[PDB]
Length: 260
Ligand SMILES: CNc1ncc2c(F)c(-c3c(C)ccc(C(=O)c4c(-c5ccccc5)n(C)n(-c5ccccc5)c4=O)c3N)ccc2n1
Image 1 (cartoon, rainbow, N blue to C red):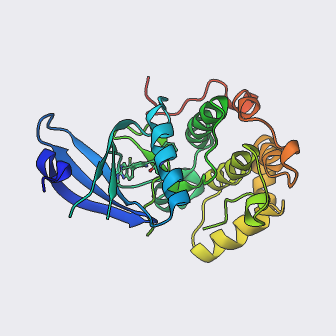
Image 2 (image 1 turned 135 degrees about the horizontal axis):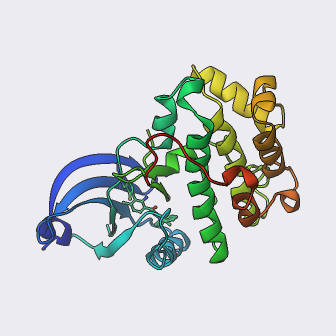
């Protein structure tokens, strides 16, 4: 048996694992570029397999500055079936890591945080404009290109339900509005640095229930209102992504070092 993966690529390292998958960094021999390659073991469940095959076809159609860049997908059946998915390689440190390395207010300057958030919201608006949704938006699914461009995807590098809409937690039917709820908590978290995991969990749990730290409401009155709206228990009451991105807070964002 000839393995397409082993023939075409030089493996570099394991980047991680999660769900049906394992992810490698590998260099393509012909083009000399390094990629992230996800190897998904197809499940022994026909309905789950149906979903996997649909999802790869869907992701292959997507092109947007804030969405992970697709290259190829293929199947291998060594004498178990594996689906390989080849994407652009992002930096090792994702948004969760980035926030964990910036634990002071000085390291979360408003314009920087809003610039990062805007890119996430724009990726979400793109999905919604295509009649798609993310469903699992959270900092561990938000990475950066080598040049710090925000990239949204379904990464599956398990190292949480904190960002999940109430309707999803309860196992109810849902709409694209689930992503708006996730966005609300992410906006808050970007603006509000933590010193401990315990502090993070307690505060984000309170924020889910619209209980905000007084110093956040005072420092960021505009974003406070935005987060409140995004975290409405009623999905109908949450704003569309397009209305979030058109908010006045996102106008003429600048910071020293910003790409010009
Ligand atoms: C440390 N650096 C680094 N860099 C890039 C990575 C990467 F692109 C991925 C990655 C890979 C290799 C493949 C697909 C994705 C991805 O976003 C996926 C996506 C996806 C979801 C939303 C937008 C775009 C893509 N889907 C739908 N799926 C998927 C889900 C269920 C079944 C089958 C496929 C994905 O796997 C991905 N993020 C994983 C880890 C990475 N690590």
